[PDB]
Image: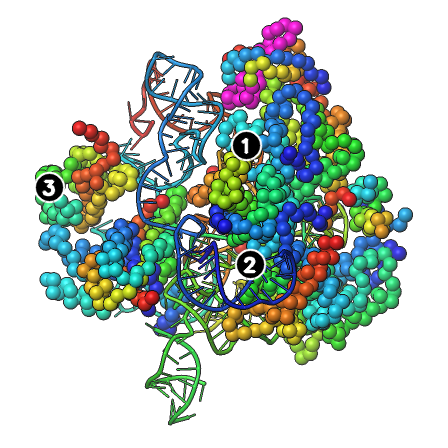
RNA sequence: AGCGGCGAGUACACUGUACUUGCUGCUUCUUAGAGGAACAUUGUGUGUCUAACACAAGGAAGUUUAAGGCAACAACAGGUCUGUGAUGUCCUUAGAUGAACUAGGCUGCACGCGUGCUACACUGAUAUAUAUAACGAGUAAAAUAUGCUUGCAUACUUUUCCUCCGCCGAAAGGCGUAGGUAAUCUUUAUCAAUAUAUAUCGUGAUGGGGAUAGAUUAUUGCAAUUAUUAAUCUUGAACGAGGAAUGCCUAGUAAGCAUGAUUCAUCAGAUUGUGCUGACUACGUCCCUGCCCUUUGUACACA
């Protein structure tokens, strides 16, 4: 009944790790035509996942120096991303983006001992990865969000070495093995 | 033709002048009312324009200025404020007091609520200074008017 | 006949006059489409779909806007129109559908009927930020 | 087409005519824009197709703009107080005019001239 | 790289110098493995592991 | 002597007799130094 | 993209029922075709506002001004050149000093007001001191709005 | 007839007296008028000497003004105000006819 | 450095990368082929 | 001040619409005069089943609902006698350490150290249009004429705030006026920006960046010179995100964006308040540092 951007009802969702869907909290109660819902998000810890994934992407994308807080140029950036990703892949881009986020690549971390990550912190870290990838992709080089996807996020989806998540995973695993 | 806010500012400064004049002249008696002796006060005011904490503090300031023993003076005024009816009184005297080393003595008796807006409402303040041989002496008089009723008090028959 | 309701979130305030007519819902003079940002036009359009065009075809709603942020004003408008439709359902048109309308409203969202209390807290002393401090040296 | 040498460096071919004529002189781009408009050069076209006739037009425009309709307030070097009147005098001999003013300041030897000689700020940089 | 299955059964407790570390037992073959996790976790969860025989410390 | 009605020398404080740090808000023409203690007698309560 | 579905009943009885930007461009083109007012010549060497500090780089800015002044005159029954300056305020980046607001030039709006007075679109009376559209100007904008409305309708 | 003061209880009691007198006299009296309250804010800083952590205080004074209208002789209402008024409250008199 | 020119999916960035030209002249080429950022047609 | 009605409709819908001019059904809506509402409230659980906290729900209010203010006991030999005709003691007083007047300095710079502003760009630089607030704060002087010879003496309103208007000049600002000692007039049926969309460019120290100086017009000031402020043009520095090091940060809060008040004849790049864009996360600890308590050892007690 309620769709997204007047185009996507997203009636098909992959099972994934059967926890990421709950974390993104996609439901008719959270079905909103356009992103950036200004609802309360910091009442408890459980409601951290209650914020929809679509809202969270645009709530995190706005972080780069001067443009902290704008979020509207960020919405344009991710919208053009959506458009070009649908251009180069003839399928529902929502599931493609969800799959790319799932297979981001840095599932393992090492700080001191290597420890696991809860699904909520996992999706938080994944959105952080897409944020930093977008930043390092849009920094200069005479290239735009089209390039940002076409050589950061498709790389993060298909496990290409050009992606920042994959190279940082390589160094993290190497140093983890070097320690133990 | 004066604006209301500036008019109230003028009223405030005039009443500040009035209160400092009351402090300057009212010396021989306590609070006996205000006018909105007496003849000369009214004449001077017109020419220029065109129990009690203050009384107890003034009495003790006279006692210490006369040179009588500070301990006896404060004990007597403390007896006086108890007999007037306050649950307690706090007197602070700061200055030379026989030594070049500045010192102060505190006198504890009564409830002595010391913070909070209910405390500010139910407790008033008196503070003065007096001249002596080698400087000034500052006196703080704190009396708490017997408590509407104090919120901290709880009692049911 | 005619009812009046109010909606307040943030600084912005909004009124809603619900009257009978032919479907003349005017945001003062400018229509509910010429606001410009389609992103907030979607939130403007959201309440209409969950109710139905036919119900609003019989009502004329006068919308008055008076200052405020872009998001605050649209949220206050949504509050005002929600209160107005609830009041007019309870008053004139139909009560039985009002129960289902409020049920589906509270099912979908909570801020549609009653807004938030979040507001600019008076910045304290210590820094340019509301909860920040000036950089200190040694 | 590209890289057209003139009195000053005018390698501006791919970039637009307005910036092209700012680069040579009048880099503040307001005088450059108004003189381009007076010469009636469409800025939509780029600077890779500049013609010698348009170059002649722009130099003739800048030659004594007082006879033209550019107002004296927009026209730089309004007075330069003396027995006569001057104008904006573009580039090399404009720098000559500026250094002539500097030497006249030196020989006048006032406080600002002394500060210029010492290499200090005029108002005061507050280096305390 | 490569990740392998682990089952989170019981939240034994919280540890660490900052309170963001929850003690957990994993599921290898080898049913015992003293691991730690960040964030809120439930009973009967599915996680991934780095290495077979890297043993942690109990606090 | 050239008494002028403008600037620093135009006015002086009523109580402290020093025109330095005079606040002219509401034309009170009182020094802030004395205002610190005159705030209660002036009737202008400090709440928050 | 520019056309959006409308669920409520419209009136299309004035300029308030249409987009401001598109109508402003359409009326600027109409005035360009009509040659009702001059460029004017004296305004070619002057930027739009002090804060703008450079050329508008659009070669239609005066006609956009002319198509917006009467739009805002209809929106607010009584306003003036000061209100127009406040509405079209921009930024004055004073170099190192932090950015601030700045009103646009007032003489160009005064000249536009003179041109509209000569055209008869606006009248001045002691009562309702702010500028208001005359009756014939209101009918003219009503006809133009109802005409562009049907054009963008079908 | 309008009144102005600082303390709210005084204006409340005299307004109650005003409505009681209006009801007793049975005049063409307008409804109570409740103007928005005005807060007068000033800033100050403690520590008369510059030493120490400079801290500031905010002092607010709250005005209180209300209005009413009556259709009666001015002398009786002004005598009533005089006998039932506080010297700390200021009142202006404006009459109405119909 | 910039070394693109003007002499010889219609999205601006993609066609600019394909033809090795500036995006302004790429927009000009887009309009020429058809006959500030907007959604895909 | 708002919700309404009708006397006339400006053009259209069709069997009111945006907008005016005049009176008054009413006061949830603009606002406060008081009161209540919120108390781990209820239940599923943790607890020596006592003191407690968690989950879910009604609910605007479930870390006291959050920001504020009062800050004990006592101390620093912490800051101020440059805030006072509050203040002891010592010192000056006619060639004054009293007061008044001219000019200069606190603004000068081989340099070093703190708080800040603008930037190092394409989520960017530039122009054009839409949607936009609150706290605000606001009335012993001009000119004229007479006599003497432009200045002095003499008399008439108040010129001594923000200001809408109609013009003069891009502008600064000025001219004669509406309003207001003030929810009425500035102004607030509205004062900003980050946005929004289209257009010039298109990441090349460039058109970014605006240090620097030159040419100037106007106001503030009897005085702008050490160019107060300022509309314009020209001038075009470093700067490719910053080593050892360091500060602030838990939700309308970080961060970014603006705006009112303070001192003001004039001048915020300072401080305070107001509003907008509403983020990345923790939801706990003593590893660093700073305090608290207990035990212990002291040859320290100005510790």
Kind of element beneath mark 3: helix
Subunit bearing disc 2 = D
Q: Position of residue I30 (x, y in %)?
A: 82, 48
Examine the residues drawn in magenta and state their main secondary structure. Answer: loop
J35 vs B59, left or right, is: right
Residue furthest toward the top?
E30
**Up/down of G44 relative to A11, above or below:** below
Picture quadrant of residue J60? top left
Q: Position of residue G84 (x, y in %)?
A: 59, 63
Residue span colored magenta: E16-41
Q: Position of residue D102 (x, y in %)?
A: 66, 66
Q: Tell me the residue at 68%/29% (across/down).
A: A11
Subunit bearing disc 3 = B
Q: Are marks 1 and 3 on the same chain?
A: no
The crowd level at tag 3 (other Cα within 10 Å; few <14, some 14-19, many 20+) is: few
Query: Would residue A19 be counted in the magenta stretch?
Result: no
The crowd level at tag 2 (other Cα within 10 Å; few <14, some 14-19, many 20+) is: few
A45 vs F22, left or right, is: right
Q: Which mark is residue B6?
A: none
Whole-angstrom CA distance, mark 2 to mark 3, is 70 Å
Foreground: G27 or H26? H26
Q: Are marks 2 and 3 on the same chain?
A: no
Kind of element beneath mark 1: helix
Residue carrying label 3: B84
The crowd level at tag 1 (other Cα within 10 Å; few <14, some 14-19, many 20+) is: few
Query: Would residue E36 be counted in the magenta stretch?
Result: yes
């Amino acid at each position: 009944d309620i769709k997204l951007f007047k185009k996507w009802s997203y009636e098909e969702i992959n099972i994934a790790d059967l926890s990421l869907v709950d974390c993104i909290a996609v439901s008719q109660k959270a079905c909103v035509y356009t992103p950036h819902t200004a609802g309360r998000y910091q009442k408890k810890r459980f409601r951290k996942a209650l914020c929809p994934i679509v809202e969270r992407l645009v709530n995190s994308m706005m972080m780069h120096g001067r443009n902290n807080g704008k979020k509207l140029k960020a919405i344009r950036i991710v919208a053009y991303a959506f458009e070009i990703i649908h251009l180069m892949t003839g399928e529902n881009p929502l599931q493609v983006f969800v799959n790319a986020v799932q297979k981001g690549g840095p599932r393992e971390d090492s700080t001191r001992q290597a420890v696991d990550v809860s699904p909520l912190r996992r999706v938080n870290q994944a959105i952080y990865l897409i944020c930093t990838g977008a930043r390092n992709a849009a920094f200069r080089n005479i290239k735009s969000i089209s390039e940002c996807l076409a050589e950061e996020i498709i790389n993060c989806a298909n496990e290409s070495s050009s992606s920042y998540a994959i190279k940082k995973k390589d160094e993290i695993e190497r140093v983890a093995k070097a320690n133990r | 033709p004066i604006s209301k806010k500036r008019k109230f500012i003028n009223d405030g400064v005039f009443q500040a002048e009035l209160n400092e004049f009351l402090a300057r002249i009212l010396a021989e008696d306590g609070y006996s009312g205000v006018e909105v002796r007496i003849r000369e006060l009214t004449s001077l005011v017109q020419k220029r324009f065109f129990l009690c904490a203050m009384a107890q503090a003034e009495s003790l300031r006279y006692k210490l200025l006369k040179g009588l023993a500070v301990r006896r003076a404060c004990y007597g005024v403390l007896r006086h404020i108890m007999e007037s009816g306050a649950k307690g009184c706090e007197v602070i005297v700061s200055g030379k007091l026989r030594a070049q080393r500045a010192k102060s003595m505190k006198f504890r008796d009564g409830y002595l609520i010391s913070t909070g807006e209910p405390s500010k409402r139910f407790v008033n303040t008196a503070t003065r200074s007096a001249q002596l041989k080698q400087g000034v002496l500052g006196i703080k008089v704190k009396i708490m008017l017997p408590t509407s009723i104090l919120p901290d008090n709880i009692s049911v028959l | 006949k005619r009812v009046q309701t109010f909606g307040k979130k943030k600084t912005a305030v909004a009124v809603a006059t619900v009257t009978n007519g032919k479907g003349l819902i005017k945001l003062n003079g400018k229509n509910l489409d010429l606001v410009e940002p389609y992103i907030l036009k979607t939130k403007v359009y959201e309440p209409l779909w969950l109710i139905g065009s036919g119900k609003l075809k019989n009502l004329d709603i006068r919308i008055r806007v008076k200052g405020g942020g872009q998001t605050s004003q649209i949220y206050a408008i949504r509050q005002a129109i929600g209160k107005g439709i609830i009041s007019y359902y309870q008053k004139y048109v139909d009560e039985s559908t009002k129960k289902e309308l409020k049920d589906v409203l509270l099912r979908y969202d909570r801020s549609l009927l009653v807004g938030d209390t979040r507001r600019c807290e008076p910045k304290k002393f210590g820094g340019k930020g509301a909860r920040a401090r000036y950089q200190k040296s040694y | 087409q590209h890289i057209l040498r003139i009195l000053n460096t005018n390698v501006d071919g791919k970039e637009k005519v307005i910036i092209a004529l700012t680069a040579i002189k009048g880099i503040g781009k307001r005088m450059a824009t108004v003189i381009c408009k007076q010469a009636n050069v469409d800025p939509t076209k780029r600077a890779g197709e500049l013609t010698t006739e348009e170059i002649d037009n722009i130099v003739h425009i800048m030659s004594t703009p007082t006879q033209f309709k550019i107002p004296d307030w927009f026209l730089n070097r309004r007075k330069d107080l003396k027995e006569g009147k001057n104008i904006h005098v573009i580039a090399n001999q404009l720098d000559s005019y500026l250094r002539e003013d500097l030497e006249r300041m030196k020989k006048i030897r006032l406080h600002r001239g002394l500060r210029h000689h010492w290499g200090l700020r005029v108002r005061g940089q507050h280096t305390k | 790289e490569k990740s392998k299955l682990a089952k989170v059964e019981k939240v034994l407790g919280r540890t660490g110098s900052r309170g963001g570390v929850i003690q957990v037992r994993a599921q290898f073959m080898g049913r015992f493995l003293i691991r730690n996790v960040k964030g809120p976790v439930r009973e009967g969860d599915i996680l991934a592991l780095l290495e077979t025989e890297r043993e942690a410390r109990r606090l | 002597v050239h008494p002028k009605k403008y600037g620093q020398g135009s006015r002086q404080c009523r109580v402290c007799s020093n025109k330095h740090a005079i606040i002219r808000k509401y034309n009170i023409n009182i020094c802030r130094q004395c205002f610190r203690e005159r705030a209660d007698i002036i009737g202008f309560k400090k709440y928050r | 993209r520019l056309l959006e579905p409308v669920p409520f009943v419209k009136t299309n009885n004035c300029i308030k029922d249409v987009d401001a930007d598109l109508f402003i461009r359409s009326y600027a083109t109409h005035l360009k075709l009509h040659n009702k007012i001059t460029y004017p010549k004296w305004c070619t060497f002057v930027k739009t506002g002090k804060g703008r500090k450079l050329a508008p780089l659009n070669e239609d800015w005066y006609f956009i001004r002319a198509s917006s002044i009467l739009r805002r005159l209809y929106l607010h029954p009584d306003i003036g050149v000061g209100f127009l300056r406040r509405q079209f305020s921009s930024k004055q980046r004073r170099g190192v000093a932090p950015n601030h607001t700045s009103l646009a030039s007032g003489k160009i709006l005064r000249s536009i007001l003179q041109q509209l007075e000569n055209l008869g679109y606006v009248e001045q009376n002691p009562k309702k001191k702010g500028r208001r559209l005359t009756t014939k100007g209101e009918n003219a904008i009503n006809n133009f709005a109802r005409y562009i409305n049907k054009k963008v309708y079908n | 007839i309008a009144l102005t003061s600082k303390n709210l209880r005084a204006i409340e009691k005299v307004c109650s007296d005003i409505m009681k007198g209006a009801k007793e006299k049975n005049l063409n009296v307008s409804g109570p008028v409740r103007l928005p309250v005005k807060t007068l804010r000033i800033t100050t800083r403690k520590s008369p000497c510059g030493e120490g952590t400079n801290t500031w205080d905010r002092f607010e004074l709250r005005i209180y003004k209300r209005l009413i209208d009556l259709y009666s002789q001015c002398e009786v209402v002004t005598q009533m105000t005089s006998i039932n008024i506080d010297p700390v409250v200021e009142v202006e008199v404006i009459i109405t006819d119909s | 450095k910039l070394n693109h020119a003007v002499f010889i999916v219609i999205t601006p960035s993609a066609i600019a990368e394909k033809y090795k030209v500036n995006l302004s002249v790429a927009r000009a080429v887009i309009n020429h082929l058809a006959d500030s950022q907007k959604l895909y047609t």
